[PDB]
Amino acid sequence: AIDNGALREEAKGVFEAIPEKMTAIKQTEDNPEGVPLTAEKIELGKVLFFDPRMSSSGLISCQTCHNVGLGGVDGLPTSIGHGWQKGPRNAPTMLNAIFNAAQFWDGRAADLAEQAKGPVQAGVEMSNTPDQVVKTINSMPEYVEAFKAAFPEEADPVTFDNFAAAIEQFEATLITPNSAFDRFLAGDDAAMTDQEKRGLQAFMETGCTACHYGVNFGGQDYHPFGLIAKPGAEVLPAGDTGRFEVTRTTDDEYVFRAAPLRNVALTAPYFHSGVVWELAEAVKIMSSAQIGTELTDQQAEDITAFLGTLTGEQPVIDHPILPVRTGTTPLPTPM
Amino acid sequence: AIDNGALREEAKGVFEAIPEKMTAIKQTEDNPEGVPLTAEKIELGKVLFFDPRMSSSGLISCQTCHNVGLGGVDGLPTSIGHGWQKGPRNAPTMLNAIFNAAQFWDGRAADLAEQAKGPVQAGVEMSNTPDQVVKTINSMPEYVEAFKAAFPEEADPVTFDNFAAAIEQFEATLITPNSAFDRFLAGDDAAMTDQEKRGLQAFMETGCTACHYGVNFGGQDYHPFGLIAKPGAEVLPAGDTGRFEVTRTTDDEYVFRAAPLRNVALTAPYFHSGVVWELAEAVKIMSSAQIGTELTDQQAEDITAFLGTLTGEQPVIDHPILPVRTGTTPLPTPM
Ligand code: HEC
Ligand code: HEC
Ligand code: HEC
Ligand code: HEC
Ligand SMILES: [Ca+2]
Ligand SMILES: [Ca+2]
């Protein structure tokens, strides 16, 4: 009941593979070469991503909530940050985030550099200020040396904007090539089991591809959560109106960015609300809410199996050795 | 001033270099062969050390408080754990902890496997139970497979004792060879500056080696903090009586394990109380309190420079890719 060639041909018309490596970002028709990724900026960004002294507590880094061992997420319903404060939304992965059209569940940041300024300043996340970050960095000569070399022409290289640019460069390399689906797409019939291929068939036939398409199986545009039927009160909490918070436009109530499904098997729990632990349940909810069809248990299990083939090679990251604090480095303030 | 040969001979009589590698642990007079380290147990212990699902919150791992990029510590006055609860003591490094005679500031744990059971269960740390840890592990087939292979001679390999043994095996590899001091000791006269050698000389001549000796420059036995003169109430809080809590022997009032000084330049703030940020001030406090000698600014700076030569090669650790949770994995309970 499986036609590999047919399945592959349909899939190539709507999805594409994650690239093997990244060398530039922000390529447009207007600026075709884009912004080069540099070894110095990637390395600086890695150090900063793992440095919990970028938070006011001294205890929270990006890695705290975007754990590179847990698919780039924290595995909690919603994140817990400074002072144990609980946030409103589930932490999405930074893996492959570079390919999404906008960042956050409501698309309120245009790119990774704009995004990175948010957690630093948010009271429920790192609860810090831009000038505190700069003063912290400037207190450690190895960090200053790195910024001066990474941003070589600038009179003022150690800036919050450049902190964000370095993090963006590092995150642009956090991609996950060679998932079983990408290997099947490239020609290996044996890369996926029959059940996983039945799931791929069902995902394409049911209409999931209207919102989950391209390189990231999502992440490109915005849709009501409940296009055809509302999900429950716990899954769609009434107080989080999604895109409406950004656009203040009537049609945008409970409109969210389509989740990019790469590595979804690693990033439970699901949806922006984080109350659905079972991926098969998220699949059933999506069919009911977005398409108005009830999936059979077999179709939901098949689709869930298929979604597992979107797990790519996870980055192997040696934890950086952080610069040592000096006498005027700001003291941690967890309390 | 400095005669390298006499200095080296003196130092060799009281200290030892960190070994290049480890292949066995718990080598004692009774059992000189010890216990072999195995690749399978080391790897399993690495995964466990970085897995925040070993805490009840789902957010706190060993690495949270013993950050491999910060010299194996959190860099806070005292640690902050489950629920943002602040603990009574500064977190010591796990680097080279394998060489210490006992673990914790009061020596209450005999070895690293016994130690590891403590943070798992402490309310202010990981706030979990042994049964939940075992059930969490058993819910993930990759973990079960690893335990069965790491402990092949056992019918019940997935136990809390074996969790602790695997962590111990991993931590035994977290040693820091080839510090400048060790390189000097091995015959490189040029490995240390003149000032560092003056510091070494002063460290030996002032009396510090009565308590800070052997491979780890401490960690081997217990002494009053205030042998000669009491330190201030902030440095020695009245409510933490140290070893007395363990033995209930009144001779042990305010008695602590001599701190092992390896990597001390990386692990501010200092003492069990974590209120002294400046290493040179800790050096002055130790001279006044333990010896009854007031160091000059120059002697304190020289000794502090020498202590910097105890920083070894920091482990370069690839962050592990953690097993994926399944349907019956216990849910995180941060709230
Ligand atoms: C937990 C307390 C967090 C910390 C610390 C950091 N992030 Fe995070 N991140 C968190 C949440 C809850 C969210 C979703 C918020 C929303 O309103 O949508 C995010 C989002 C991101 C993203 C967007 C990815 C996407 O939408 O697909 C990125 C790229 C990201 N976070 C990166 C990032 C960086 C670089 C951090 C250190 C400066 C950082 N985050 C910290 C939770 C938490
Ligand atoms: C647009 C009209 C959609 C269609 C058709 C499908 N999905 Fe979707 N999906 C969409 C959005 C806007 C979101 C985010 C909703 C939110 O606010 O949380 C999602 C999310 C998912 C998820 C969760 C992924 C996560 O990281 O949490 C899954 C597993 C998912 N979608 C799967 C899925 C399936 C299998 C579909 C066809 C049956 C389907 N979606 C259709 C938008 C749209
Ligand atoms: C912060 C909330 C912690 C977590 C999580 C873990 N540890 Fe820790 N550790 C912490 C403190 C405050 C202390 C000192 C407590 C005392 O009473 O002395 C320690 C101690 C250790 C040690 C002893 C090292 C020494 O005394 O030189 C080791 C080896 C150690 N901790 C390891 C360890 C492991 C393996 C953990 C995960 C299971 C773990 N700790 C978590 C703070 C915190
Ligand atoms: C035994 C009587 C000691 C003598 C002599 C010296 N030290 Fe010591 N040192 C001792 C103990 C019991 C402790 C732990 C005290 C506590 O409760 O915190 C220490 C600690 C240090 C430290 C702090 C290291 C840390 O990781 O926090 C330093 C820097 C230190 N000791 C240095 C030092 C110097 C330079 C000494 C000679 C002048 C000296 N110590 C003597 C026990 C004893
Ligand atoms: Ca999620
Ligand atoms: Ca310390």
Image (tube, coloured by chain):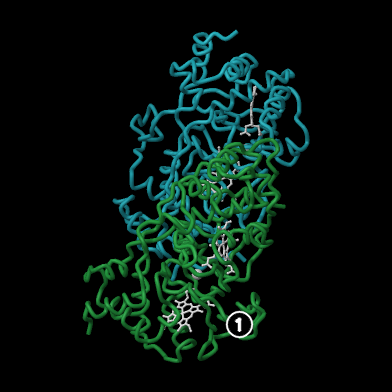
Chain colours: A cyan, B green
Residue at the image point whose x is 47% and y is 68% from the top:
B29
Q: Secondary structure at mark 1?
A: helix
**A127 to the left or right of A130:** right
Q: Locate residue A273, reporting x and y percent.
A: 69, 39
Q: Assign the C terminus of chain A to one quadrant of the image.
A: bottom right
- Ligand 2 shows up in the quarter that is top right
* Image quarter of residue B23: bottom left
Does the numbered disc 1 mark a residue whose Cβ is under 8 Å from ligand 4?
no
Q: Is residue A197 above or below residue A245?
A: above
Q: Is residue A90 above or below residue B15?
A: above
Q: Nearer the viewer, residue B248 or A61?
A: B248
* Image quarter of residue A284: top right
Chain designation of label 1: B
Q: Is residue B56 above or below residue B267?
A: above
Please identify the residue farthest to the front as the structure is shown: B30
Residue type beneath disc 1:
Asp
Q: Locate residue A108, reporting x and y percent.
A: 57, 40
The answer, for residue A119, to whether it is visible in the render is no
Q: Locate residue B247, reporting x and y percent.
A: 64, 77
Residue at the image point whose x is 32% and y is 58% from the top:
A145
Q: Nearer the viewer, residue B234 or B219?
A: B219
**A292 to the left or right of A30:** right
Q: Locate residue B224, reporting x and y percent.
A: 54, 84
The answer, for residue A186, to whether it is visible in the render is yes
Disc 1 target residue? B252
Q: Assign the N terminus of chain A to one quadrant of the image.
A: top right
Q: Nearer the viewer, residue A66 or A110?
A: A66
Residue at the image point whose x is 62% and y is 59% from the top:
B117
Q: Is residue A241 above or below residue A203?
A: below
* Image quarter of residue B85: bottom right
Please rate how many residues cluster around mark 1, counting C-alpha atoms within 10 Å: few if below 14, some from 14 to 19, many from 20.
Answer: some
